[PDB]
Length: 126
Length: 126
Length: 126
Image (cartoon, rainbow over all chains, first blue to last red; front, top):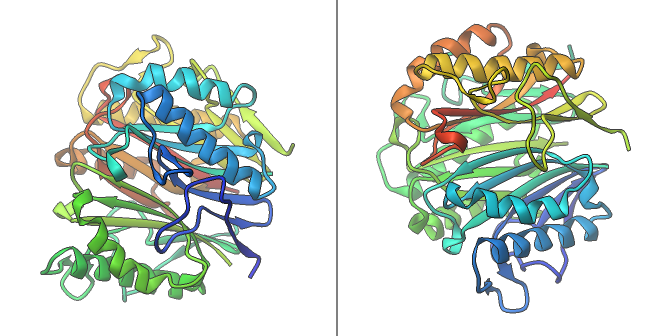
């Protein structure tokens, strides 16, 4: 009832039974985003840094569409194909969460959708 | 204090230090469910589709026991043993979340409890 | 705005763009903790049981610093390097959550930060 679907054309269009995000009042639940360019609907060319920047940009557009801001991210779930890429991922991530950074979970998985190097999901509270 | 344990005999009986779900007012936190038949306490026979249907049925019974409905699922965490099974998993999942589908996180893990093909945990808000 | 960063010297000091936890009113989001001894900033010597006890102690100190208690843990995300260690992990975990235990998600990942055997993140509500 107070649950709302969030959609923006500025982040990858959901194909299937999920929403980019679900807003319930001052809480936002954001889907695990992968490095899809919304212009092509395919993974962006580049290394972990380019992919991380694409993911966080996807998340930023979703969060902003919902009336939230990156500052409202309380908890981030970070899934890496390769934990050795952590330092490089982290240097880009640090750009987006400079102050009052969210709680974070970081693990290495064996594979991601579209063979992504990284997927990030967040929960926000404003 | 306003935290409540949720239990139903219609979903796998917890063996150990966890609850099927925890309800706090209009928010429900649901344990990662695996394809256990509550009748046998063992994994159901069948492929990813049969296992996915068992998991979602387990989640549905927990959610309903708690006074919630699948419509209240805001965020789903989906862990697959094999990302190549995604399309098949998704065809069953799509049956349970037809309208206003939840935010979703989907990754491939190296192994699950009882060597399950899939485990799903959800957060709901009503 | 009502979002607050949580920090205690009694749990591993964040190095980088994350907070040990984020408190928003009666909800706490806690980072995935690994078996770092805050005295050394390195992984503790020992098997899964010693590592699990270090992780849960880290989580306990964060939760207490925030004005919460382990009793307020609603949902735990448990990531194991090796699912065969589950029974041993569980025997220690059972010590910390004796009554009204949280909802739990448990999966095996291919690797963790610092090659940890286990990482745990929690969400609490008081």
